[PDB]
Amino acid sequence: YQPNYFLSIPITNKKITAGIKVLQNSILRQDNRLTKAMVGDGSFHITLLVMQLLNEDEVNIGTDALLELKPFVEEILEGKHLTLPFHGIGTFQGQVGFVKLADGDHVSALLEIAETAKRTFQEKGILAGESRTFKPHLTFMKLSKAPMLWKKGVRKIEPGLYEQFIDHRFGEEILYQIDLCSMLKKKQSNGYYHCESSIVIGEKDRKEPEDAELVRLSKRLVENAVLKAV
Amino acid sequence: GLTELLQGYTVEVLRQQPPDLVDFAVEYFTRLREARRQESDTFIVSPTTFHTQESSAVPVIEEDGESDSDSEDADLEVPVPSKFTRRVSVCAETFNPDEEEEDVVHPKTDEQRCRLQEACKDILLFKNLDQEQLSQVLDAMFEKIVKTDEHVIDQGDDGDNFYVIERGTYDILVTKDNQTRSVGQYDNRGSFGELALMYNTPRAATIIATSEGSLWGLDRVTFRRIIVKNNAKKRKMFESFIESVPLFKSLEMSERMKIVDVIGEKIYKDGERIIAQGEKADSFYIIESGEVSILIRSKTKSNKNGGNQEVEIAHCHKGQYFGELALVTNKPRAASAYAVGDVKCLVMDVQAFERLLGPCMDIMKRNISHYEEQLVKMFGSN
Amino acid sequence: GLTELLQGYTVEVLRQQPPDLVDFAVEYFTRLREARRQESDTFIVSPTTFHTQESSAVPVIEEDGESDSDSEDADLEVPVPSKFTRRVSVCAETFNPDEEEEDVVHPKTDEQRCRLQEACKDILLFKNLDQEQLSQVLDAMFEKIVKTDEHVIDQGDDGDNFYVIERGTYDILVTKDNQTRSVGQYDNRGSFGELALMYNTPRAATIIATSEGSLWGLDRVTFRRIIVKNNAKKRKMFESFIESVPLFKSLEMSERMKIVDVIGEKIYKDGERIIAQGEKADSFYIIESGEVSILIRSKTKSNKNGGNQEVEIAHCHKGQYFGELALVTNKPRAASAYAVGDVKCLVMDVQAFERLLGPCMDIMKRNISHYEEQLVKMFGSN
Amino acid sequence: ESVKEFLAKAKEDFLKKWETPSQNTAQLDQFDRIKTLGTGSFGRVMLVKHKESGNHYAMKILDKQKVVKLKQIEHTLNEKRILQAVNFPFLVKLEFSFKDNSNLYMVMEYVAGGEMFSHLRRIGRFSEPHARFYAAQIVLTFEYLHSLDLIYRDLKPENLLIDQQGYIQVTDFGFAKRVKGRTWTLCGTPEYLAPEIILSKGYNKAVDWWALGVLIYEMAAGYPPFFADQPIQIYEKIVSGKVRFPSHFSSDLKDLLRNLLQVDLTKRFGNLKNGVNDIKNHKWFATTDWIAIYQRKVEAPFIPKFEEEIRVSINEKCGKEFTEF
Amino acid sequence: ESVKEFLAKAKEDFLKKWETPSQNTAQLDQFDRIKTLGTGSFGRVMLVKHKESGNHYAMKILDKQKVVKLKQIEHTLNEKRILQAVNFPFLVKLEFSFKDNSNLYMVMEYVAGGEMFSHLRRIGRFSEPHARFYAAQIVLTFEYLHSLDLIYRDLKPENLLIDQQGYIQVTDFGFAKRVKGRTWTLCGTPEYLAPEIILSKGYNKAVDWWALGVLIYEMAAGYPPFFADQPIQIYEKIVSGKVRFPSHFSSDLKDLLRNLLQVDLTKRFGNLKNGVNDIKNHKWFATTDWIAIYQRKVEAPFIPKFEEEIRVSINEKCGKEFTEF
């Protein structure tokens, strides 16, 4: 089926979106007619779940299902933040360019969240999810967005264009907000998709409300140093 | 362990803000480095059992089976069957008794023949045969030479001959059921197989020669034919002498044959007395050869005395009879009778005659037109 | 440096795979810990100095201008008119001639003063000065010592003094246009700068000493004041002696001054003749000191002869006059006049008197009520 | 008396059938076939039923060819001529006779009864009254037969049948022969042979009476008077005439038997002047009603208990000699 | 004669103005300003025009303060008192006088004519008739002045102007002084100084007549009688009185000049009994009509050819002494 709505994980880490802006611009200085293929500033996201919401009631139902999903995602994470590392570049058959999600324990957790999301929405009467394997990625360009490119000889993304960013660490996004977004409505002023509703996973997010305080950071500093040593 | 180890260090760096991170690391891990454990636990656990109670279930079925069993048992065969199936008739070969028409030559010395007679005295079939038949029979006996080890007769085999031993030794054997016994021997004497002269029947024993020997043999058929022929000839001859006697003319054929059946024969040498005057009259005679003189001592003629000598009243020949009065009276013989030369007479007992045909007087009257004649003959003058 | 420290340890843990991470940390950080060498630096002088503040924003402006340029050769132009060539007035410093009220001491030996007089004989301003004024003037001359090489006067400089050489040698120089000539020398004799005694004017030459020397100097103002004062005193004094003479009473002030202007003075030693009887009467006298004896040789009294000796007609003193008749007649002197002791008389020439005031007879008549009296005085008895 | 009447009429009836044998009477297709009891050791006798009347008969199968061998072929061609010419109540009957390529088939009457030999042997011996009952029947039968000059010559328990009425019926005329005068074949059964037969003296009616004496003795004793294990001894005893009677034999019986078992023909009952009356009038037969026995009116003392498919030759064979039949 | 009349009326008119100087007469706002010819080496003289009448005058600018220095401040305060009190046809005129913080401003008459010095020097020398013409004017002027006991003391071509009518007009009263008796300042011009001045004997009217002798000589010769390159020599010649006359000088002239240039005061013309008549009646002046010259009716022999903005002090300064003005 053709989805018209999706659950979105927005990219809020400014380093990630700034790195992608650089990537997009470097491609454009090599070939400026790729301009309309680039995804818009402010639109960067990971799609968690696609669906069809076909009327006002169903849009309300989607919003209800998103709210109902919150405790489930909290259950799944078992008191740990979900960290999504974005590293390197890939394509879907040379037509869609994306920043890759790095391999790790987070991928299975993300998949679990996606499947629980699909179940939660379907149990509320919403056609959601797909039969194909969930392969999350962070899109930065799509040739289909610029139809005149075929019409003038550009029919695939030249792999040389993004060669320098092939092992570029864009940054890490911690899961917090999940948005219910319209694919077809007018985008927000800041470039992001039209949002019907949002939830926040985070507590926000800690096992304990009271400050440690900053005791955990030692964990973040160490984990990051180990990741860099690899 | 790597992240946790470095987290303890990094917490202390953040808390304590040391000016030299490396020196602080040497101190922290050295103090950590001693690695003494205040307490440790090592444990062994006994097996633990948890008990649950399981859920019930219901099964429903009904089954019916029907069958019938029978058994049998077996026993030893005895008792064995007891009954015996049959008995049988016997029959010799038939033969036209009446002489067909004159149409066996085996040489024998006086000693041999004389010895054969002796060997045959007691055999029942031979025992009471007349002189002639015995001669014809011995004449018919053929010789059979036997070499040692030879079987004269074998038990079971059909029999046709009777044998008299002439020379040699023989062993006799008899098989009873599965057993064979050498029961007896013969040493240049003996005879056996007499039964074969009557009819054909299985040999009851086996006889084997134990040396070169010789046996006189006689075939049944030859023996029976000699005897029947001779007795049938004798019968015809007796019949004739009775028939020509006028006193018996009223007799029927069958009545004459009853006489022939029992009537006797006697031979008298010239001069010997046949009937003595005075003794009891029991029979009558019919001369078949020779002559007979009838004498009477003339004393029984008055009252005490006289002649007391010899007087010939009559003189009979072939075909005639005398002593007839014994048939019609019961007084002592009136006169004596002597054989005139060699004589052969048929002798009939009066009492037997009566038992068979009744009193002679009735026979004489049967033919009434000759009754007187008969009477005058019997009690008359001449 | 915290993340980098933790990373470096982790890299070696991943490479070496130590079973005991704590022992590996002790050894790693101990080996790391010495960590030579931390830094290198160079130290130099600023050199530090005070300075005005370095930075300002810069305004931007647009402007336009126009110019006039004059180009010329350059010349000294030393000489320029100077068109006149016009004679200019001169003027000395003014001064109240009439003696203010008595209210210069420079020692000098007889030889020195005597020598100063000699040196001044020919100088026009000094040439005809009376005894007294010359004395007062020399008195006023101050000494000026000069060392060799010193400039007494320099051409062009303003002048105030006149100098007389006392000792030393000097070179005189005169610059004409651009040329300077050593024109002459002085050797312990000389004087110069006389013009300075008249009015202030530029020195016309330069005088330089060529040895230690001494000069007598005189300042204009001092010189003029000495002279004017003295001549104004003399005038007042002459005026008085004329005024007290009754013959001249009808004279007007200005008429007496014309006399004062030209009238002479004479000194006579006791006994010497002033007027000789018989010679021509040309002037008259007015005694200002001493006495005069008037004698007449009594011969001109008859017709040839007599007295011919000496007789005193009159005897005059301070304030009186004699020889008056020369003013009203033209006959030889009647008598002689001799000085009685030391005498000082004012001497007036009659012809000059007439040219200035006209004949004396008219003056005597001016005041008619005294005409007779005057006449009797002049031509009378006593 | 009627005795003469009967015999006279009897001889008439017999001479007529004797001098004109009733040949091939009935047809084989009138009789079916049932069981087949006729083996043993000779001949083929099989039971059979009738058509219209539907009666039971005993048919003897004699293959025309089977003959010629054996012992004789006349002792039969003659046997047939007699059975057909005779008629008596205690004699088996030749009901129907016929032949043709099959040839010589005897349709004998059938009495579903018991054998005399089996009965006598089982019970051992008969009481004298019972023995006298059977004896009378044989005396009468012999008087009839001898009246026709026919001698049986094979009397014995084995040849006597007890019919369903309990009366005797005589079978097997193998040795039966018409003889006026004397005959000579040595035949019969060992135990029952007469001295004259054993010795070949020639004989006629007297042997049947001797046999009767043997028959009566065995019935009342259980065993024959001249028994022995060896045939030779039997004959020597027979010739000696010496007889030993059981203890239980009555006087009248012993006397009758001494007269029947007479080696001396001048003293043998039946052979003397009065013939069969010497027997009929004997004290042992005093309680006998001869007419009653003849009409079978007396009550018998014992009522007895009561395969393949051959074909012709489609052609007559030995009929070139067995004409007379 | 009228001579006495004139002088009498003259002294009257003079003593009146002398003993009551006409101070600060006109106002500076009645006069404008034109050119500015008044430099040289002292003083500030600038031309100017009048309002109502619209006349031309020569105004001398004397800064009240400028004074006090220089050589003297009375030779002026006195100079002003004289110019104002005198009235003669051949004398320049003080038209208007005024001061106040500016103070001391001289409004002199103006004659657009030529200088005597320039004219004489150009043509070399005047003919005797022409010289006599100018001389007469100076004699008359001196008679007037001496009548008032005033001595000029600075006679010379340089101080004489030739007006548009060709008549002389005397200027610069710097040394003019009223003296009855004797005076002593050594002043004038070298060439024109009298022996008595050079020698400080005291003097009065006689020096003006001596100067006239010098003035007449120079006009008729072209050069002064006691000329020399050095001032000292000039004076020594002056004192000796010895004079040498050019060849062309007439007798009457030489005689007149010997009498004017008399070192001997008892013989000098003008100083004797008859005063100025000894001069007026001299043979050299015989063809002179004194009245005619006075009324300027005679025909002259030669008709001549014809900056910044200062301000007051808004306050009067040296007025604490220059009161009299």
Image (spheres, coloured by chain):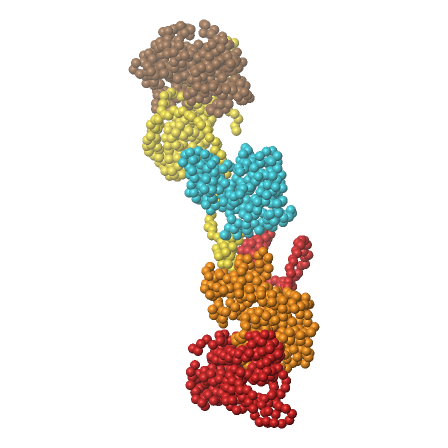
Chain colours: A cyan, B red, C yellow, D orange, E brown
Q: Which residue is at 45% across, 7% downward? A: E3
Which of the two residues, E76 or B20, is positioned nearer the viewer here? B20
Is residue E225 found left or right of D151 in the rendered image? left
Residue C63 spot, x, y in % from top left: 44, 27
Q: Which residue is at 59% across, 82% downward? A: B380
Q: Is residue E221 visible?
A: no
Which of the two residues, A162 or D155, is positioned nearer the viewer here? D155
Q: Which residue is at 47% across, 40% downward? A: A96
Check the image and report above or below for B48 versus D212: above
In this view, which residue lies farthest toward the left?
A: E247
Rendering quarter of residue A121 = top right
Residue B152 spot, x, y in % from top left: 46, 82
Check the image and report above or below for D17 versus E280: below
Which of the two residues, D107 or B180, is positioned nearer the viewer here? D107
Residue C203 spot, x, y in % from top left: 39, 29
The mark tally for this picture is 0
Is residue C248 found left or right of B52 in the rendered image? left
Q: Which residue is at 44% across, 30% downward? A: C219
Residue E110 spot, x, y in % from top left: 44, 12
Which of the two residues, D3 or D268, is positioned nearer the viewer here? D3
Q: Is residue A146 visible?
A: yes
Check the image and report above or below for D236 versus E101: below
Rendering quarter of residue B72 = bottom right
Rendering quarter of residue E275 = top left
